[PDB]
Image: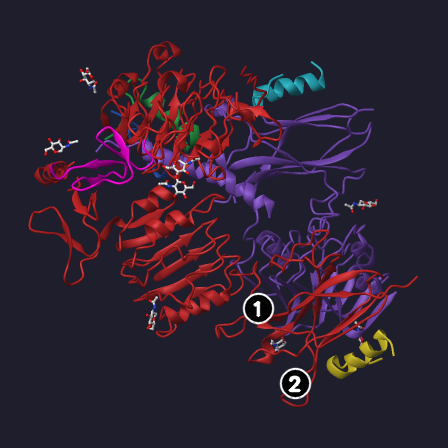
Chain colours: A blue, B green, C cyan, D purple, E red, F yellow
């Protein structure tokens, strides 16, 4: 989930972008 | 860049997705 | 600023508590 | 005066048991300590045990819930191992529950001259202190097979934390404004708060755990502080601060500030700084913050969906 | 008029306000009402927009980062009941980081049938202390309302309205400056009253237009059918979604939809209800869409994503409702000071078997794991790393597992693990070691001797004070001898004494607190093993610090070496109130 | 006894401590 991806690890800008239309 | 948590995950995603908006299934 | 006034300004700047 | 322990193996277990040892320059035979409570203590453990400089036997500290620091042994500088506890130990800290400072090794040169070290449990006590002792006390250099356990030591303790610098120190005769560096754990919500500590302290020989026990004697006027309103931009993290109130003119305060941080460990602490002015319930609060963090993390995990 | 408008699926409205016109007609939402992530909007966008047709959401309402929404008196003026059939986390109403929300406007809201309110981080939100949440929902304690403007600043909540004694003074209860809180007489506590105060019919959840008239009522306490509230669905109406009655052709149609293609649940009929899956031990028969009990076992296996499922709150638990077999490992991580044991019991109680490991980690308010009512097997097919099949870590109020006097839990493979369970006594862990069969196969269970139960009274044997003698300043006590099965495991006794002016002292919890009014613990090295196996050495202790005219609670505890033997738990006395003699 | 005297007696009897 987002909190494992971005909060408890480092999200690449690709990974943040993966959550949007 | 950094750990995005709390509101800052919401802010950061919003900036990435200002007019596009967030996904849902 | 005075020490007290500056702290209040700092508190608004930092913690968001403003007189 | 020299104190030959007639029983050879004295236990100190309250203030009134230590007063047997008042004025002991050295202690023959071993000591055990099991100091477990006390009231309005007035440093009465330091006074009785401060004079002691050399202990012949082993030094055993067990169950000793009240003691936070062993600095009451102000002059202690030698354990001789002329009577080792079984296992050949010369120092033995078992289940000291609030022991936080073994000794202030900067000002302490204790040498446990023979036999091994022992450290089990003592959750508050840091492995750093333990490692400092075994090298200060020759044991590790002497290839003593020291029995210290990584598990159960330093657990539930904010050990090995980052330094906080003070950036700003602006005084008045009766109030002092401080700002320290911004500090944030990897997740900023783990900063539950800071906690300032201050102490009117005419001498620059103060130590964090001096004059302190877990039976509620505490020389420090602790002031817990809310976390600052975080910036997105790291270069716009304002230096947090406090205006500590009600001081006395031309009095030198010892001060430090420390992070209050929820376990996921990640924390920071300042050095003691000196400023001359001018001429449990806790586990509920640490849960509540951890609970609101948990909800927020759940909401994010649920509302934000990765497109397939 | 009861629900004079459509019934709509769960609504997610995000990014753009446009989607809210899906609510234009709905009077009941059969699902969640998520409204969130509308950064772009302004109060300009919410000036007109209102859904007074909406009366009741079956699941939960979630408002999160919606901007320019100043008050919910615009959007949902007539909303009255959030049923909470499915919750968000443990919450039915959630209002989170609502940046501009000035004052809650859900004046009509009268009931939340299940789950709590969370209203957090609404930095401008006043008018919260005015609301009387006790009227809205039973579980006020679980309600979580923090970090709002009413919690940070002064609020000028003048409402020139019913005043309740929930607050210390007689504060008027008001949703907004315009709207009183609709308090209704104590006798009508869950169905409400008309404007003249004449109570509603017994079904009329929250409010009614015309009194004691079950079609003129705003919402249904039990069920909706054909424009009337009904206590239960009469045949041939099956209960659907626990709030309305549907006929067989309705359930049959839905069953064939999810048969024909899937987003899906075929709506089989069991127990006069319409449910997503045929329950454990039943199968759908003959294409009649009627669950019939199988011959031979046919449990409801619930299959877990990548072999793990973490139960953090009610909603995570409810996802396992009726899942009498778990084909995966289970992690329980309940957080917060609110005990969800009842909710866990409803959902996790029916789980007869777990295929993976069972892990309880960082569970705060979980006193017991007895919410599982019939868990009998932890197959350990997958294991927690370290080959564990049962894992319990950091559980802060855990006091007992399953009561081993009654329940049986077995592990087909894998070890036990127990660390940092402060109130869980090793007694209740060692009994598991036997019942589970790990001891039988000699699994090297990683159970910490001195991290489990250290903060709980653990002594199961008893010590009695053979002999009391007292002085003006001294109390000489002796008690019956004790030795564990191996006397070498006796480290000593511990005599606890305290002042006790009134004999209302409660037992020692176990936490050794050193506070000003806490137990004066005295450690006591044990007597000499001597003479007959009668152990004719009654231990004793004399205390000399006492004062005349003073009654003191005393008890003794043993102090004992725990071991892999598992047979040493120690002994403890009851508290005895002894009194020193009085001298001038 | 006296509470002290018996206590001295108890210590010799059980704990083996004597003056
Ligand atoms: C809200 O309305 C519901 C009815 O739908 C009430 O629910 C019952 O309340 C009692 C306690 O008052 C519980 O023991 C029952 O289990 C509840 N039943 C159901 C079906 O939920 C509820 O009490 C009302 N709350 C308020 C504050 O009026
Ligand atoms: C301790 O006491 C014994 C007996 O009195 C004595 O032999 C010994 O030397 C003493 N210790 C030291 C360090 O002198
Ligand atoms: C203690 O030390 C002596 C000398 O180093 C050694 O002979 C003895 O075996 C040791 N005993 C134990 C139990 O460590
Ligand atoms: C510092 O030294 C003084 C004596 O000069 C002493 O009174 C004081 O206690 C010392 N500081 C501490 C923390 O013990
Ligand atoms: C709501 O009602 C209007 C007019 O009755 C209709 O056009 C519309 O399709 C209905 N549904 C929605 C989702 O707006
Ligand atoms: C009840 O059944 C009839 C046909 O028997 C069907 O037309 C109707 O839609 C059903 N009820 C509802 C509310 O759909
Ligand atoms: C537990 O086991 C005993 C003995 O095998 C059995 O008789 C009993 O029915 C079981 N009870 C439960 C609640 O499973």
Q: In the figure, is residue E441 to the left or right of E459?
A: left
Give the vertical position of D203 relative to E8 (above or below): below
Name the mark on residue E268: none
Could you say where residue E487 lies in the image, as x and y percent from the top left? 60, 80
Could you say where residue E537 lies in the image, as x and y percent from the top left? 70, 83
Query: Mark 1 — residue?
Result: E459
Q: In the figure, is residue E234 to the left or right of D9?
A: left
Q: Residue at x 59, y 44 (%)?
A: D282
Q: Residue at x 73, y 57 (%)?
A: E502
- Residue E161 in sight: yes
Could you say where residue D233 lies in the image, as x and y percent from the top left? 46, 23
Q: Residue at x 73, y 59 (%)?
A: E498
Q: In the figure, is residue D163 to the left or right of E75?
A: right
The residues bearing labels 2 and 1 have C-alpha atoms spaced at a distance of 20 Å
Could you say where residue E9 lies in the image, as x and y percent from the top left? 23, 30
- Camera-side residue of E108 and E376: E108
Residue range of the region highlighted in magenta in the rendering = E220-249
Q: Is residue E123 magenta?
A: no
Sequence-wise, the earlier of marks 2 and 1 is: 1
Q: Is mark 1 within 8 Å of ligand 7?
A: no
Q: Residue at x 62, y 88 (%)?
A: E533
**Dividing the picture into quarters, in which one does residue E117 lie?**
top left
Query: Mark 2 — residue?
Result: E535
Q: Badge 2 local density, few (<14 within 10 Å), some, or many (20+)?
A: some
Check whether the beta carbons of the residues at disc 2 and disc 1 lie within 8 A of each other.
no
Q: Is residue E246 magenta?
A: yes
- Camera-side residue of E528 and E241: E241
Look at the numbered disc 2 and give the secondary structure of its residue.
Answer: loop
Considering the image in quadrants, where does the N terminus of chain B appear?
top left
Q: In the figure, is residue E464 to the left or right of E110?
A: right
């Amino acid at each position: 989930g987002i909190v494992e991806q971005c909060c408890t690890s480092i999200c690449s800008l690709y990974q943040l972008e993966n959550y949007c239309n | 860049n950094q750990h995005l948590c709390g509101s800052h995950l919401v802010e950061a995603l919003y900036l990435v997705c200002g007019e596009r908006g967030f996904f849902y299934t | 600023x005075s020490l007290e006034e500056e702290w209040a300004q700092i508190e608004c700047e930092v913690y968001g508590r403003c007189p | 005066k020299v104190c030959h322990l007639l029983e050879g193996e004295k236990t100190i277990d309250s203030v009134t048991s230590a007063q047997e040892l008042r004025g002991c320059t050295v202690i023959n035979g071993s000591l055990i300590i099991n100091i477990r409570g006390g009231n309005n203590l007035a440093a009465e453990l330091e006074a009785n045990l401060g004079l002691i400089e050399e202990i012949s036997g082993y030094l055993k500290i067990r169950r000793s819930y009240a003691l936070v620091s062993l600095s009451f042994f102000r002059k202690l500088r030698l354990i001789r191992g002329e009577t080792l506890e079984i296992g050949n130990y010369s120092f033995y800290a078992l289940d000291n529950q609030n022991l936080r400072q073994l000794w202030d090794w900067s000002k302490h040169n204790l040498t446990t001259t023979q036999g091994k070290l022992f450290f089990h449990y003592n959750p508050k006590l840091c492995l750093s202190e333990i490692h400092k002792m075994e090298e200060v006390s020759g044991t590790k250099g002497r290839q003593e097979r020291n029995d210290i356990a990584l598990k159960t030591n330093g657990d539930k303790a904010s050990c090995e934390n980052e330094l906080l610098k003070f950036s700003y120190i602006r005084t008045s005769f009766d109030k002092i404004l401080l700002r320290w560096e911004p500090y944030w754990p990897p997740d900023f919500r783990d900063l539950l708060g800071f906690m300032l500590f201050y102490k009117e302290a005419p001498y620059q020989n103060v130590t964090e755990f001096d004059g302190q026990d877990a039976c509620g004697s505490n020389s420090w006027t602790v002031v817990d502080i809310d976390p600052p309103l975080r910036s997105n931009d790291p270069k716009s993290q304002n230096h947090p601060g406090w205006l500590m109130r009600g001081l006395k003119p031309w009095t030198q305060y010892a001060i430090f500030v420390k992070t209050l941080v929820t376990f996921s460990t990640y924390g920071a602490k300042s050095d003691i700084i000196y400023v001359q002015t001018d001429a449990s319930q806790i586990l509920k609060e640490l849960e509540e913050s951890s609970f609101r963090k948990t909800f927020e993390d759940y909401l994010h995990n649920v509302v934000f969906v990765p497109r397939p």
